[PDB]
Image (tube, rainbow over all chains, first blue to last red; front, side):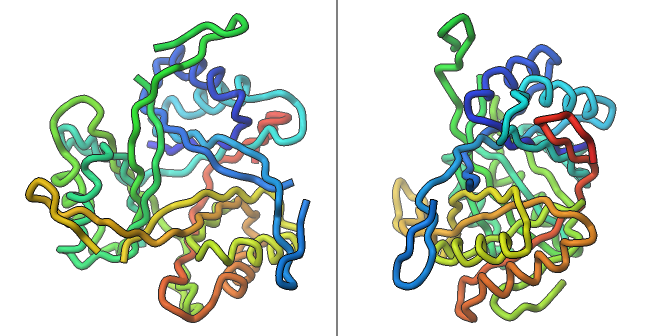
Length: 104
Length: 104
Length: 104
């Protein structure tokens, strides 16, 4: 199993969600994060006064499906412009379904 | 070392926290994320207008303790009903204590 | 490639950001999370009524740079006092640049 994580432009969330569902991928979770590009001095130190909003999507997928999921996310999240973001795949050592306690 | 991550129902957070403390596990962090189940068309595209609130808990645990921690989280977070979520274990390659700079 | 994740005190975010930029590291994202230290009984159960705010920073870095980045984050985020947090390095199995579709 692999954890697929992607940092995408907020307005691309629905396209990515649609792409994943079409593949029959379930279990996506999303949250807001911030990136940086615009600074102001306060008490001798520099403070960022502007941020770029992003959405972080995370979904666990089988070894046999992850490459297809990664390709699908990339195609859906792409604009070609600055700030499009990244997709990272991490190996999962163990996964548990909380509802039943089943492992792997 | 292992990073244990769990996506749980929000009302289960306190049970999970209690379970972990009873094991003497410290260093839990939590944040809100969203899952999906309820769509509306805007400018020709489908937009989700409803979400399922979840809580993501993350805690680093030793190789000798992680299986016990995973079992404890599962038991505490379980309802048996739809939406109970998942627990993922990821291998940590290096860990640093910021307070002292100690590694591993 | 490695994913470097750090849970730091919120007031240390700008120092960490400055340290990383000085190294020429790009692609940092940040979000708020909560840790725990202060409980109240509601319907027979214990509820936490206080939390410690933290910031979670995540950045992907090359194998050749990660140790330097980890050292830099630790030095910048350190106060020496309780609650300073942790840095975790996770192996990345695959990375994709969404803007161009390039892999690794």
